Amino acid sequence: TCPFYKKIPGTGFTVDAFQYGVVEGCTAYFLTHFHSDHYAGLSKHFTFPVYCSEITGNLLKNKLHVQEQYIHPLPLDTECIVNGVKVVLLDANHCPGAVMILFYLPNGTVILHTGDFRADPSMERSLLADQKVHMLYLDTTYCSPEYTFPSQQEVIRFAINTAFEAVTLNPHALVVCGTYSIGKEKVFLAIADVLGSKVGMSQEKYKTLQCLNIPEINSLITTDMCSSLVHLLPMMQINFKGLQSHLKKCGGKYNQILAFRPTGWTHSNKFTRIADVIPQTKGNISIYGIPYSEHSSYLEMKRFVQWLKPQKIIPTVNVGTWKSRSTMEKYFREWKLEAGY
Ligand code: NI
């Protein structure tokens, strides 16, 4: 059954609630972003209104074949009315098209549901600065102090230099990058840009990326593997067996693979700096695990909540265990006591 943290009090609304059949009482389904845990359930046969960003709209139309009449795309940073309720979509600094939703309830309450997000200080100067927020439905994926990780800028620096170095030393070397959902495009796009190649991918993934309103994207991507020396693969195929295999498919055009796995957090972050990361190497194949996150670090999250000063916090990730729930309320109370709200 639809859980309580996917319903919006005093509205006919749910968020990211497509895997529970018809929800008793819902007049509008919101979808924060196109990642399968959140869209799970949607298909061409869905006949209720869905609300979302223009980019999430393009993917529902083209990848899930949802009928155009049930897709209601909204512009960001703009006050719109949905079944008599003022709402605003804001950028979530997660994957392309990913949004936060502000709900202005008829009774005077104000609610912010973050979807998935990576908190930034730039958010402190959106339409969020203009008014109080009473409830915050918060992406809590990394709500624990051991969760540190570097900036996206630092990580893209690392990958660029690494890639450019290896290829200038050995021009017959192939760069491979893993993927399974949208998001983190900057990794492979930045490597291809410094190398002067487009990014070879499967047709299904070229179709995915074509839906994203990226600037000049035609110039950056291709389905022609042979012309390209930066290749996308499934994240499943990024291991020694899968790379030796793919290497053979290229027909003696390359002798060395340098591959990147963008992970979220990994326990080498508690000890190691980004500058000191090393690969796993078996012969002519090396694999880099890089901590590119599109989710708030503990500090980034902490900062955002203490600036927002909400009256109630309702977690949306790591809610399935009592130890987790308990631990998260402990940090919330600390943040509150430390900041005085
Ligand atoms: Ni997500």
Image (spheres, grey):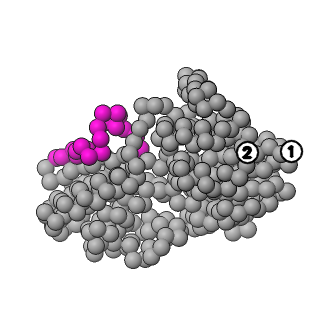
Per the image, label 2 sits on a secondary structure element best described as loop
Q: Residue 132, which numbered label?
A: 2
Looking at the rendered structure, the kind of residue marked 1 is Asn
Q: Position of residue 211 (x, y in %)?
A: 53, 68
Q: Is residue 300 above or below residue 334?
A: below
User: What range is drawn magenta here?
Assistant: 264-282
Q: Residue at x 58, y 28 (%)?
A: 338
- Image position of 332 (left or right of 264): right
Per the image, label 1 sits on a secondary structure element best described as loop
Magenta stretch containing residue 35, yes or no? no
Looking at the rendered structure, the kind of residue marked 2 is Lys
Q: Can residue 245 be seen here?
A: no
Q: Earlier along the polypeptide chain: callout 1 or callout 2?
A: 1
Quadrant showing the N terminus: top right
Q: Position of residue 63 (x, y in %)?
A: 56, 64
Quick one: which residue is furthest to the front in this view? 340
Of the residues tagged 1 and 2, which is closer to the observer? 2
Q: Residue 107, which numbered label?
A: 1
Q: Position of residue 231 (x, y in %)?
A: 31, 64
Other-residue count near label 1 (Cα within 10 Å), few / some / many at <14 / 14–19 / ≥20: few
Q: Residue at x 66, y 46 (%)?
A: 113
